Length: 63
Length: 183
Length: 120
Image 1 (tube, rainbow over the protein chains, first blue to last red):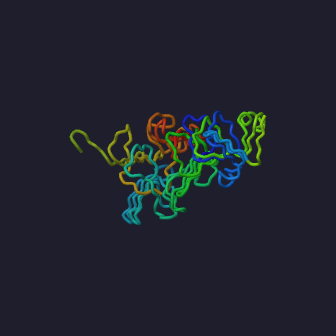
Image 2 (image 1 turned 180 degrees about the vertical axis):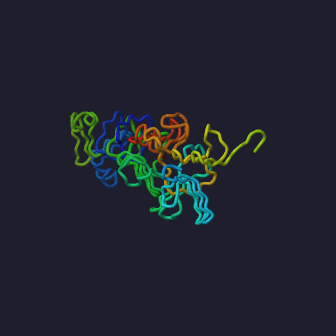
Image 3 (image 1 turned 90 degrees about the horizontal axis):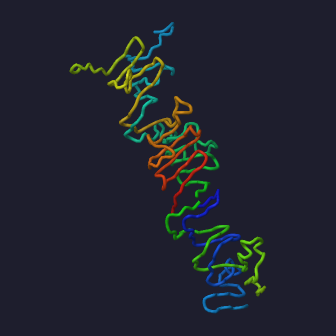
Protein backbone atom coordinates (compact mmCIF):
# COMPACT_ATOMS: atom_id res chain seq x y z
CA UNK A 1 0.00 0.00 0.00
CA UNK A 2 2.84 2.38 -0.88
CA UNK A 3 2.53 4.21 -4.21
CA UNK A 4 5.44 6.61 -4.50
CA UNK A 5 5.69 10.04 -6.12
CA UNK A 6 8.66 11.40 -4.14
CA UNK A 7 11.83 10.68 -2.14
CA UNK A 8 11.44 9.63 1.49
CA UNK A 9 13.69 10.56 4.40
CA UNK A 10 11.67 8.43 6.79
CA UNK A 11 11.20 10.16 10.15
CA UNK A 12 9.63 7.03 11.66
CA UNK A 13 10.75 3.39 11.77
CA UNK A 14 10.76 1.24 8.62
CA UNK A 15 9.92 -2.27 9.78
CA UNK A 16 8.96 -5.31 7.70
CA UNK A 17 8.68 -9.11 7.57
CA UNK A 18 10.01 -9.84 4.05
CA UNK A 19 12.01 -8.00 1.40
CA UNK A 20 12.59 -8.44 -2.33
CA UNK A 21 14.59 -5.89 -4.32
CA UNK A 22 17.13 -5.46 -7.12
CA UNK A 23 19.88 -3.68 -5.15
CA UNK A 24 20.48 -1.66 -1.99
CA UNK A 25 22.66 1.40 -1.37
CA UNK A 26 22.62 0.97 2.41
CA UNK A 27 24.63 2.46 5.28
CA UNK A 28 25.18 -0.33 7.86
CA UNK A 29 24.15 -3.96 7.78
CA UNK A 30 23.21 -7.11 9.63
CA UNK A 31 23.35 -10.74 8.44
CA UNK A 32 23.59 -13.41 11.15
CA UNK A 33 24.45 -16.53 9.16
CA UNK A 34 25.49 -16.15 5.54
CA UNK A 35 23.10 -18.14 3.41
CA UNK A 36 22.73 -17.23 -0.24
CA UNK A 37 19.83 -16.62 -2.59
CA UNK A 38 21.59 -19.44 -4.38
CA UNK A 39 19.67 -21.21 -1.59
CA UNK A 40 17.28 -18.53 -0.29
CA UNK A 41 15.18 -17.88 -3.40
CA UNK A 42 15.97 -21.45 -4.31
CA UNK A 43 13.90 -23.86 -2.24
CA UNK A 44 15.01 -24.47 1.35
CA UNK A 45 17.21 -21.41 2.11
CA UNK A 46 19.40 -24.02 3.81
CA UNK A 47 19.58 -25.68 0.38
CA UNK A 48 22.20 -25.66 -2.36
CA UNK A 49 24.99 -23.35 -1.23
CA UNK A 50 28.78 -23.67 -1.27
CA UNK A 51 30.04 -21.90 1.87
CA UNK A 52 28.07 -20.57 4.83
CA UNK A 53 30.01 -17.96 6.82
CA UNK A 54 28.27 -17.96 10.21
CA UNK A 55 30.02 -15.32 12.33
CA UNK A 56 28.68 -16.74 15.61
CA UNK A 57 30.78 -19.86 16.31
CA UNK A 58 33.97 -19.78 14.20
CA UNK A 59 32.03 -21.40 11.37
CA UNK A 60 33.67 -21.29 7.92
CA UNK A 61 32.27 -24.29 6.04
CA UNK A 62 33.73 -24.49 2.52
CA UNK A 63 32.17 -26.58 -0.25
CA UNK B 1 -49.68 44.15 -13.32
CA UNK B 2 -47.17 45.25 -15.95
CA UNK B 3 -47.44 46.34 -19.58
CA UNK B 4 -49.57 43.81 -21.44
CA UNK B 5 -48.11 41.05 -19.22
CA UNK B 6 -50.32 40.35 -16.20
CA UNK B 7 -47.44 38.80 -14.29
CA UNK B 8 -49.01 36.84 -11.43
CA UNK B 9 -47.09 35.70 -8.35
CA UNK B 10 -49.42 34.49 -5.57
CA UNK B 11 -52.42 32.23 -6.06
CA UNK B 12 -54.86 29.95 -4.28
CA UNK B 13 -57.54 28.13 -6.29
CA UNK B 14 -60.69 26.52 -4.90
CA UNK B 15 -60.89 24.09 -7.81
CA UNK B 16 -57.79 21.95 -7.30
CA UNK B 17 -56.35 23.21 -4.00
CA UNK B 18 -53.41 24.66 -5.91
CA UNK B 19 -51.15 26.99 -3.92
CA UNK B 20 -48.75 29.02 -6.07
CA UNK B 21 -45.98 31.47 -5.21
CA UNK B 22 -43.47 33.29 -7.37
CA UNK B 23 -43.29 33.80 -11.12
CA UNK B 24 -43.96 30.82 -13.36
CA UNK B 25 -41.42 29.14 -15.62
CA UNK B 26 -42.83 25.62 -15.76
CA UNK B 27 -45.84 24.70 -17.88
CA UNK B 28 -48.15 24.73 -14.85
CA UNK B 29 -45.78 25.21 -11.91
CA UNK B 30 -43.53 27.74 -10.20
CA UNK B 31 -40.37 27.29 -8.10
CA UNK B 32 -42.22 27.24 -4.77
CA UNK B 33 -45.74 26.64 -6.04
CA UNK B 34 -47.58 23.71 -4.50
CA UNK B 35 -50.22 21.08 -5.21
CA UNK B 36 -51.67 19.26 -2.18
CA UNK B 37 -53.75 17.36 -4.73
CA UNK B 38 -51.43 14.53 -5.75
CA UNK B 39 -49.51 15.91 -2.81
CA UNK B 40 -46.02 17.30 -3.34
CA UNK B 41 -43.84 19.66 -1.29
CA UNK B 42 -41.81 21.51 -3.92
CA UNK B 43 -39.22 24.15 -3.00
CA UNK B 44 -35.72 25.16 -4.08
CA UNK B 45 -32.86 27.43 -3.09
CA UNK B 46 -31.93 28.97 0.25
CA UNK B 47 -29.79 32.11 0.46
CA UNK B 48 -29.14 31.67 4.18
CA UNK B 49 -28.60 28.20 5.64
CA UNK B 50 -26.82 27.95 8.99
CA UNK B 51 -28.61 24.86 10.31
CA UNK B 52 -30.25 21.51 9.70
CA UNK B 53 -31.66 18.87 12.03
CA UNK B 54 -31.67 15.68 9.96
CA UNK B 55 -29.01 14.69 7.46
CA UNK B 56 -30.67 15.56 4.14
CA UNK B 57 -28.54 12.79 2.67
CA UNK B 58 -30.69 10.12 1.01
CA UNK B 59 -32.34 10.58 -2.39
CA UNK B 60 -35.78 9.07 -2.95
CA UNK B 61 -38.88 9.17 -5.20
CA UNK B 62 -36.96 6.44 -7.10
CA UNK B 63 -35.69 3.63 -4.91
CA UNK B 64 -33.07 2.57 -7.45
CA UNK B 65 -32.66 5.35 -10.03
CA UNK B 66 -32.46 8.28 -7.61
CA UNK B 67 -29.23 7.17 -6.02
CA UNK B 68 -28.88 8.43 -2.41
CA UNK B 69 -26.00 10.84 -2.86
CA UNK B 70 -24.53 14.27 -2.25
CA UNK B 71 -22.27 15.05 -5.19
CA UNK B 72 -21.13 17.56 -7.79
CA UNK B 73 -23.88 17.85 -10.39
CA UNK B 74 -22.59 16.78 -13.79
CA UNK B 75 -19.80 14.47 -12.60
CA UNK B 76 -19.66 11.00 -11.07
CA UNK B 77 -17.56 7.85 -10.61
CA UNK B 78 -15.54 7.49 -13.80
CA UNK B 79 -15.17 11.04 -15.12
CA UNK B 80 -11.81 12.58 -15.98
CA UNK B 81 -12.89 15.86 -14.37
CA UNK B 82 -11.52 16.83 -10.96
CA UNK B 83 -15.02 17.09 -9.48
CA UNK B 84 -16.43 15.06 -6.58
CA UNK B 85 -19.12 12.48 -5.88
CA UNK B 86 -20.22 11.04 -2.53
CA UNK B 87 -23.08 9.10 -0.99
CA UNK B 88 -24.86 5.76 -1.46
CA UNK B 89 -24.93 5.10 -5.18
CA UNK B 90 -27.70 2.66 -6.07
CA UNK B 91 -26.80 1.71 -9.65
CA UNK B 92 -24.18 -0.35 -7.80
CA UNK B 93 -26.31 -0.49 -4.59
CA UNK B 94 -23.41 0.85 -2.49
CA UNK B 95 -21.43 4.09 -2.15
CA UNK B 96 -19.41 5.41 -5.05
CA UNK B 97 -16.90 8.18 -4.51
CA UNK B 98 -14.10 10.12 -6.17
CA UNK B 99 -12.21 13.21 -5.00
CA UNK B 100 -9.82 14.90 -7.41
CA UNK B 101 -8.61 14.23 -10.92
CA UNK B 102 -8.15 10.91 -12.76
CA UNK B 103 -4.43 10.51 -11.93
CA UNK B 104 -3.77 12.14 -8.51
CA UNK B 105 -6.94 11.51 -6.52
CA UNK B 106 -8.80 9.06 -4.28
CA UNK B 107 -11.36 6.71 -5.82
CA UNK B 108 -13.76 4.47 -3.93
CA UNK B 109 -16.59 2.06 -4.59
CA UNK B 110 -18.82 0.56 -1.92
CA UNK B 111 -16.67 -2.57 -1.86
CA UNK B 112 -13.13 -1.39 -2.64
CA UNK B 113 -10.95 1.72 -3.03
CA UNK B 114 -8.26 2.94 -5.44
CA UNK B 115 -5.85 5.61 -4.16
CA UNK B 116 -3.06 5.74 -6.76
CA UNK B 117 -1.14 8.43 -4.84
CA UNK B 118 1.67 8.76 -2.30
CA UNK B 119 2.22 10.50 1.01
CA UNK B 120 5.24 11.61 3.01
CA UNK B 121 3.65 6.37 1.17
CA UNK B 122 4.22 4.96 4.65
CA UNK B 123 4.15 7.46 7.53
CA UNK B 124 4.52 5.54 10.77
CA UNK B 125 3.05 6.17 14.22
CA UNK B 126 3.23 2.60 15.59
CA UNK B 127 4.90 -0.83 15.50
CA UNK B 128 3.89 -3.23 12.73
CA UNK B 129 3.52 -7.00 12.99
CA UNK B 130 2.69 -7.27 9.30
CA UNK B 131 -0.10 -9.79 8.68
CA UNK B 132 0.38 -9.55 4.91
CA UNK B 133 3.46 -9.85 2.68
CA UNK B 134 6.16 -7.16 2.68
CA UNK B 135 7.48 -7.05 -0.87
CA UNK B 136 9.73 -4.46 -2.51
CA UNK B 137 12.13 -3.68 -5.37
CA UNK B 138 14.86 -1.72 -3.55
CA UNK B 139 15.98 -1.19 0.05
CA UNK B 140 18.14 1.37 1.85
CA UNK B 141 18.51 1.31 5.63
CA UNK B 142 20.95 1.80 8.51
CA UNK B 143 20.72 -1.67 10.08
CA UNK B 144 18.48 -4.74 10.26
CA UNK B 145 17.58 -6.98 13.21
CA UNK B 146 16.32 -9.80 10.98
CA UNK B 147 15.45 -13.47 11.56
CA UNK B 148 16.60 -15.42 8.47
CA UNK B 149 18.39 -14.23 5.36
CA UNK B 150 19.14 -14.64 1.69
CA UNK B 151 22.11 -13.34 -0.33
CA UNK B 152 22.95 -15.22 -3.54
CA UNK B 153 26.36 -13.82 -4.45
CA UNK B 154 28.22 -11.74 -1.89
CA UNK B 155 28.89 -8.34 -3.38
CA UNK B 156 29.52 -5.43 -1.06
CA UNK B 157 28.23 -1.89 -0.75
CA UNK B 158 31.93 -1.25 -1.14
CA UNK B 159 30.77 -1.95 -4.70
CA UNK B 160 26.96 -1.80 -4.47
CA UNK B 161 26.45 1.81 -3.39
CA UNK B 162 29.69 2.49 -5.21
CA UNK B 163 29.15 2.52 -8.96
CA UNK B 164 28.81 -0.84 -10.70
CA UNK B 165 27.86 -3.21 -7.82
CA UNK B 166 30.29 -5.55 -9.60
CA UNK B 167 32.88 -2.81 -9.03
CA UNK B 168 35.63 -2.36 -6.45
CA UNK B 169 35.40 -5.28 -4.05
CA UNK B 170 38.03 -7.59 -2.53
CA UNK B 171 36.39 -11.02 -2.22
CA UNK B 172 33.06 -12.23 -3.62
CA UNK B 173 31.77 -15.32 -1.80
CA UNK B 174 29.30 -16.83 -4.28
CA UNK B 175 27.80 -19.90 -2.61
CA UNK B 176 26.58 -21.39 -5.90
CA UNK B 177 29.69 -22.84 -7.59
CA UNK B 178 32.50 -23.23 -5.03
CA UNK B 179 33.49 -19.62 -5.69
CA UNK B 180 35.83 -18.02 -3.14
CA UNK B 181 37.70 -15.30 -5.05
CA UNK B 182 40.17 -13.50 -2.77
CA UNK B 183 41.68 -10.11 -3.64
CA UNK C 1 -51.66 41.98 17.64
CA UNK C 2 -49.74 42.28 20.90
CA UNK C 3 -49.18 45.08 23.40
CA UNK C 4 -48.10 48.19 21.49
CA UNK C 5 -46.24 45.93 19.02
CA UNK C 6 -48.39 45.09 15.98
CA UNK C 7 -46.31 42.02 15.20
CA UNK C 8 -47.16 41.07 11.61
CA UNK C 9 -46.43 37.65 10.11
CA UNK C 10 -48.22 37.14 6.77
CA UNK C 11 -48.43 39.70 3.98
CA UNK C 12 -49.17 40.17 0.30
CA UNK C 13 -48.85 43.62 -1.26
CA UNK C 14 -50.33 44.74 -4.57
CA UNK C 15 -47.68 47.43 -5.00
CA UNK C 16 -44.51 45.37 -5.42
CA UNK C 17 -45.77 41.77 -5.49
CA UNK C 18 -44.09 41.20 -2.12
CA UNK C 19 -45.01 37.95 -0.37
CA UNK C 20 -43.97 37.83 3.28
CA UNK C 21 -44.20 35.10 5.93
CA UNK C 22 -42.94 34.95 9.49
CA UNK C 23 -41.66 37.64 11.82
CA UNK C 24 -39.20 40.18 10.43
CA UNK C 25 -35.57 40.54 11.48
CA UNK C 26 -34.08 42.00 8.31
CA UNK C 27 -34.52 45.63 7.32
CA UNK C 28 -37.21 44.75 4.78
CA UNK C 29 -37.22 40.95 4.74
CA UNK C 30 -38.16 37.89 6.78
CA UNK C 31 -36.72 34.36 6.84
CA UNK C 32 -39.19 32.96 4.30
CA UNK C 33 -40.51 36.23 2.90
CA UNK C 34 -40.35 36.59 -0.88
CA UNK C 35 -40.00 39.14 -3.66
CA UNK C 36 -40.92 37.97 -7.18
CA UNK C 37 -39.95 41.48 -8.25
CA UNK C 38 -36.20 41.17 -8.78
CA UNK C 39 -37.09 37.53 -8.35
CA UNK C 40 -35.59 35.57 -5.47
CA UNK C 41 -36.60 32.31 -3.77
CA UNK C 42 -35.48 32.81 -0.16
CA UNK C 43 -35.96 30.13 2.50
CA UNK C 44 -33.99 28.64 5.38
CA UNK C 45 -34.08 25.78 7.86
CA UNK C 46 -35.86 22.43 7.75
CA UNK C 47 -36.67 20.51 10.94
CA UNK C 48 -37.47 17.31 9.05
CA UNK C 49 -35.41 16.31 6.02
CA UNK C 50 -35.47 12.65 4.96
CA UNK C 51 -35.09 13.17 1.21
CA UNK C 52 -33.66 15.11 -1.70
CA UNK C 53 -33.74 14.55 -5.45
CA UNK C 54 -30.80 16.58 -6.78
CA UNK C 55 -27.45 16.95 -5.05
CA UNK C 56 -27.75 20.42 -3.51
CA UNK C 57 -23.97 20.58 -3.85
CA UNK C 58 -22.89 23.56 -5.96
CA UNK C 59 -22.87 27.14 -4.68
CA UNK C 60 -23.82 29.93 -7.08
CA UNK C 61 -24.94 33.59 -7.29
CA UNK C 62 -21.16 34.20 -7.48
CA UNK C 63 -19.37 32.09 -10.08
CA UNK C 64 -15.99 32.54 -8.39
CA UNK C 65 -16.53 33.90 -4.87
CA UNK C 66 -19.33 31.53 -3.83
CA UNK C 67 -17.19 28.43 -3.97
CA UNK C 68 -19.25 25.27 -4.68
CA UNK C 69 -18.85 23.49 -1.37
CA UNK C 70 -20.44 21.64 1.53
CA UNK C 71 -18.34 22.38 4.60
CA UNK C 72 -18.24 23.33 8.26
CA UNK C 73 -19.12 27.01 8.52
CA UNK C 74 -16.23 28.95 10.01
CA UNK C 75 -13.41 26.59 8.99
CA UNK C 76 -11.65 25.79 5.73
CA UNK C 77 -8.41 24.54 4.14
CA UNK C 78 -5.61 25.77 6.38
CA UNK C 79 -7.20 26.08 9.83
CA UNK C 80 -5.75 24.42 12.92
CA UNK C 81 -9.26 23.43 14.04
CA UNK C 82 -10.40 19.82 13.68
CA UNK C 83 -13.39 20.86 11.54
CA UNK C 84 -14.10 19.79 7.96
CA UNK C 85 -14.37 21.27 4.48
CA UNK C 86 -15.47 19.58 1.25
CA UNK C 87 -16.60 20.45 -2.26
CA UNK C 88 -15.32 22.37 -5.29
CA UNK C 89 -13.44 25.36 -3.96
CA UNK C 90 -13.21 28.10 -6.58
CA UNK C 91 -10.58 30.41 -5.08
CA UNK C 92 -8.30 27.62 -6.33
CA UNK C 93 -10.85 26.51 -9.00
CA UNK C 94 -10.75 22.90 -7.74
CA UNK C 95 -11.78 20.97 -4.62
CA UNK C 96 -10.21 21.76 -1.28
CA UNK C 97 -10.67 19.40 1.64
CA UNK C 98 -9.52 18.66 5.17
CA UNK C 99 -10.85 16.17 7.73
CA UNK C 100 -9.49 16.29 11.26
CA UNK C 101 -6.86 18.32 13.07
CA UNK C 102 -3.63 19.88 11.74
CA UNK C 103 -1.35 16.96 12.72
CA UNK C 104 -3.39 13.71 12.52
CA UNK C 105 -5.78 14.25 9.63
CA UNK C 106 -6.23 14.02 5.85
CA UNK C 107 -5.67 17.12 3.73
CA UNK C 108 -6.47 17.47 0.04
CA UNK C 109 -6.39 20.08 -2.70
CA UNK C 110 -7.88 19.63 -6.15
CA UNK C 111 -4.47 18.64 -7.52
CA UNK C 112 -2.71 16.86 -4.64
CA UNK C 113 -3.23 15.38 -1.16
CA UNK C 114 -1.37 15.38 2.16
CA UNK C 115 -2.13 12.53 4.59
CA UNK C 116 0.59 12.76 7.26
CA UNK C 117 -0.75 9.73 9.15
CA UNK C 118 -0.21 5.98 9.41
CA UNK C 119 -2.35 2.86 9.29
CA UNK C 120 -1.99 -0.72 10.49
